[PDB]
Amino acid sequence: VRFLDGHTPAYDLTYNDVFVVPGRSDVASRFDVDLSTVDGSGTTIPVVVANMTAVAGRRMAETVARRGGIVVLPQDLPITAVSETVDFVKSRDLVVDTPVTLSPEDSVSDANALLHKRAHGAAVVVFEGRPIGLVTEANCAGVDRFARVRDIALSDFVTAPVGTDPREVFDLLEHAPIDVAVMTAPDGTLAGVLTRTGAIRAGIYTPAVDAKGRLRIAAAVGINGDVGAKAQALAEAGADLLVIDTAHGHQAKMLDAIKAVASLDLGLPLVAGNVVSAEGTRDLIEAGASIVKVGVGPGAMCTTRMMTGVGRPQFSAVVECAAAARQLGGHVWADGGVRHPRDVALALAAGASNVMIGSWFAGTYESPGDLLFDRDDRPYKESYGMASKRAVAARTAGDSSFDRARKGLFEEGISTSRMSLDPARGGVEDLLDHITSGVRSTCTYVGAANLPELHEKVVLGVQSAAGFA
Amino acid sequence: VRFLDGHTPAYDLTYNDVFVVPGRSDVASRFDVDLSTVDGSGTTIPVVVANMTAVAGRRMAETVARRGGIVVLPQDLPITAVSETVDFVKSRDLVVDTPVTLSPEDSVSDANALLHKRAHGAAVVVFEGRPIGLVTEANCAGVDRFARVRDIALSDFVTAPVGTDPREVFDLLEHAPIDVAVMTAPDGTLAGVLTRTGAIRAGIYTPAVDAKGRLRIAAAVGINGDVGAKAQALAEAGADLLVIDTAHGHQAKMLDAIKAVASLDLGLPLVAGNVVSAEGTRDLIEAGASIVKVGVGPGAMCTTRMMTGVGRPQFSAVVECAAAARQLGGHVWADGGVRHPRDVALALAAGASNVMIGSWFAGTYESPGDLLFDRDDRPYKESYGMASKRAVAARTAGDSSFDRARKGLFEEGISTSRMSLDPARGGVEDLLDHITSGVRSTCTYVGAANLPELHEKVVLGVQSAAGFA
Amino acid sequence: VRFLDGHTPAYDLTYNDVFVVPGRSDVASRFDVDLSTVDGSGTTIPVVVANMTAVAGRRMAETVARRGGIVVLPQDLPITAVSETVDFVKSRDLVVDTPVTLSPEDSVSDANALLHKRAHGAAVVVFEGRPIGLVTEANCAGVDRFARVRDIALSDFVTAPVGTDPREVFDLLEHAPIDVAVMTAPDGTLAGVLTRTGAIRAGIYTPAVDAKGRLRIAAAVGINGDVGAKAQALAEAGADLLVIDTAHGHQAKMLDAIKAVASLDLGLPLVAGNVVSAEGTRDLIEAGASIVKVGVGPGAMCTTRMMTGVGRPQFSAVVECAAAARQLGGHVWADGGVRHPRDVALALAAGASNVMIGSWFAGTYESPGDLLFDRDDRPYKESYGMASKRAVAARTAGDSSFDRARKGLFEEGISTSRMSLDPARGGVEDLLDHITSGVRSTCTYVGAANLPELHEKVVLGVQSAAGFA
């Protein structure tokens, strides 16, 4: 990277200690920017969803993959569930989305509970596979709790055939009372749903697909047990990317696991982490990893940094790791608690080929967790970090209760977090457009048409802490 | 600029990281300081009002121009409205101010609503053009809401002829029950109003006027469409200054627009922005711009800096841009969210020929927006940044709803802000005197009689962030 | 009236000290009850709106008269305004209602302010008299305050010709996105609006009309000045009913005024009040009054009862006055602060031919006052009793300020009241249906098909104060 003259700080830099200086630009608008990645993951946007139990679901995976991103499934998930989720994701369409199906005999409470897990705002009542009507919010509210779906269902709705151009659908929905545009297969049965915003997004985001034209998806593995067997099973299960993640990735056990997985030669890229040192990046790459995750205790007040004085500011760590990987011909991923689009933009400018997003996406409809309401009626969803204490306890396989309790004694608390959900941008796509708009604006300001040029022609600076007063 | 020995920081500086060291002074008082600018804008004070829809009105323009400042009208305003506003501003007097005219049949609520858009605190009832009386606050309050103006109007008021010396008016108002001093033309009809504070200010501030003796005013243009046609139309409409503004001013499109406007040779100075780099300043000046705006993402927690890691601290950017412009024989303007008089003083000391003020003036009576009251009865006025989403959507001309929604998807939220109004200093002049007093005190401390000497003989220093604890 | 055996209380009774005992009933449903009055006022429901400045408006008069009620205009209103209001009311239709007309150039704030004075929830934009579209709440909210009507107007709306059956309109609006059903004259211009609820009510309420088929309306007069001249002028102005009202109606001045008005023989019924004694009722009737108002200081904690120990419980006063009037062949009206439908039902059962409603209707959209919002955003409207202090001061004609202040010294305070507006039932009709439903349920419980039978076959009881603990 390039810094302004005289900017040679005597400390590591974080995202709050740097800024991007605008330069000569030839890009007309944001849409003239290509966000495709060159790390081999096949993502058309620099967004990856973290392998967190409270975030990495099936609806989340489908929604993110349809918009060009990728998702890594939790490493503790059973193999059968992993295969089922992979099949479900790869069985979806690239243009239309799976709506919520409600039985006419279902209760109003169950109706709204099943309604609030998608961003469409409506659910389709299905009888033998054919739509009868739509039920929306403010229609099931204020009515008797003993009522049923059939007593509030609206039989008038928009219908279009599959294969219709998104522009035609948007034009049709210009006077529709409900923005939903449920689509029926030529047989007549439900074959997905479309929305005007979804129709618009269909022309902006290029879905990420494999050689078979199916949405890509990733799975995670640990460093305990037979790593090679689990990796091979996941590869046979349909996983496109494999991630080996742990708190400290520079230990010899991770090197052994990486060598074991690379020996099988599954023909897929390997993502290993996390390290914050150039030596760790080189060691991981030489072990047979093509992508290296970065970020250990990136926050100055995070749990890891309070428990241990171990960590590193994200910006300098990413810069050094990316430089080492490029020297060795690899790529890096920028983990470490992304919270604003500025984080994604600066991570990309520092040299990261992709960015990993965790707890931010927890507070969304598409997340696997159930939607909760606080004392002030404001929606929220709980977060449990990488995994819950029960999850790791089960991950420790069959062991005597004495050994399990002995191992869990040193384990810290669950550290559950209540992730608020923004009413205006509660959908996952409502955050993806935000992040992509930020990145595109950064690219236009720099004057780069794609991420490699963004990294090549970026000029950075350093600011003091007096500007935050 | 000059810094103390040993002050060579390894980072860009902001307004909180610098201070002015007092030096030998020969200036007796603040009034012995000349605040005239040399940028060619004709302003007698270093204050310019930003081209914001919620700030740049007609009353605001008149009030600011009467006190020596200038105002830039919004770029999205219709040409007919621009011409009407220019004619209204140029048809005003340089000493007396236009009061509020109330019909005797008007309602009390309408009376106070029309009263609260001026700082005089009184409104003149007009019948065939002759005053009958005055209505003030606390007179229409506590009465029946069905009452009318004639039922609360006070027929006793002070009257003086036009052309009377302000000192005589102030002496006359020494025992007047109401400080208002409504002035009648020799015919008898209303020809403006005067106030003791206004009379005093008439002897301090020199109004900014053109060769015809009429108040100056400015208009803004974009970089989309036929820039030359709009610039020529505005010049013919009576605009004195032209401003070409966009988020990123170093792009080739801005250079093309500047060349197009300069080719017509309208005989007016051109203000272009915004840039934070010396290269951008040189490119803009060589393209045919005499004044360059500065400031992109100046705050470390602003919307631009959170969405993108793009920006620069205001002080260093202003210093570098001013140095480049002086090397090329130009001038610069200091934008970037002025909030305290310290900002204006430091911007002037850094080398800026003028300062641009935006959202600060939104919370004033003279602003075009309507006055609102919060839950705690405290007055406030809303702010919408440079323009509202509807404004830019209309600015995109006639386009299909699909394209408009597609373009607006990446657009961020309205980001409306509730700008509180200070009861003690709610008037625009009540902020202008504050800012000018700060600047004059800075000049006396430095020991400079005018802004060029302020820039020439200023000594600065650097402080750490530990002083803000 | 009939009381249960042994109920001979040693005190006057109020509405809280009595109840109606159900009896044998042959009425099937509420709709089988006739609410027509026999007092000669021509009202089809036992509801009369009090002559209060904050209630008796023009929209209020139209809305109440369309539903079978009558309204008495304030006595302090100018004769020209009275004639204009009478013409406006008599120029309206008996089926459709006058909507709100908004100019396309009007502001959003003005749009919603003009929208919130009617219960339809929508306003019609008019250009040369032809509708272009509809603007509703939640459409003008959340948008730029600088926007205009044309920028938010919806051009799609329901249209039907005048004369269409209300049942057809209701059937048409079954799938309409907006419940409004604006009606166009055969020429094409606006000729009123209709609503599904309004269409339903058109078949329940019989509008009150005179011999010419126009909506009836009433006006009030005082006892000061030339009462005969004002009464004759109001009769010529189109007023249908004349009311002579004052705090104490048994004084000789009221008798003189009644004799003066009756001498002219205007051919209209005379309503005089207020009295609470049988002697006062007889004296007022013999003076030439066909209807006598009842109720002086009816509340035990009202302003009149706190200032003076003068008053009487409403129930016993109404019973005695009605008995005296029936003995003399007259009728009585039940004033005295109606707040619940129980009050109307008990007043009718006691022998009152009609009921007068005052401050209750102040908190409605149709009231002349402007809608206000409190600290908790809850809507409300101010009340000023019979008249404001300014109103009575002006009513005292042209007198020296000394005499006016001397007369107003003993006058109590304005006693303004903040009448809350119920969001669910904010419309006047939304209270009329409530009151009429209460009265119809009372009639069904008693077993009476009309008010005379309600008075004839009612059995009452007495309860102690221990039931309110």
Image (cartoon, coloured by chain):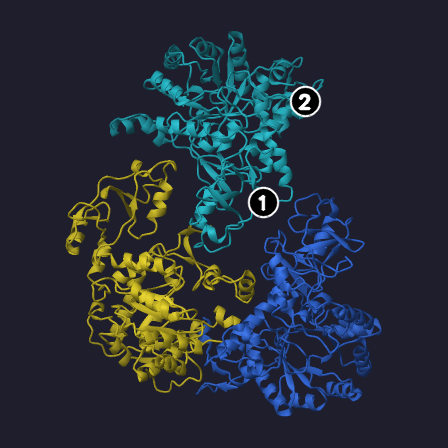
Chain colours: A blue, B yellow, C cyan
| Residue B259 against residue A323 in the figure, above or below | above
Residue A121 in picture, x, y percent from top left? 65, 56
Residue at x-position 20% and y-position 73%: B27
In this orientation, does residue B428 appear? no
Residue at x-position 33% and y-position 70%: B355
Q: Which residue of the protein is positioned furthest toward the front in this rendering?
A: C187
Res A343 quadrant in image? bottom right
Residue ID for mark 2 = C445
Q: Identify the amino acid type marked 2.
A: Tyr
Residue ID for mark 1 = C178
- Spatial separation of the CA atoms under disc 1 and disc 2: 38 Å
Residue C20 in picture, x, y percent from top left? 64, 20
Give the number of marks.
2
Q: Identify the amino acid type marked 1.
A: Ile
In this orientation, does residue B426 appear? yes
Give the structural element (helix, strand or loop) at label 1: loop
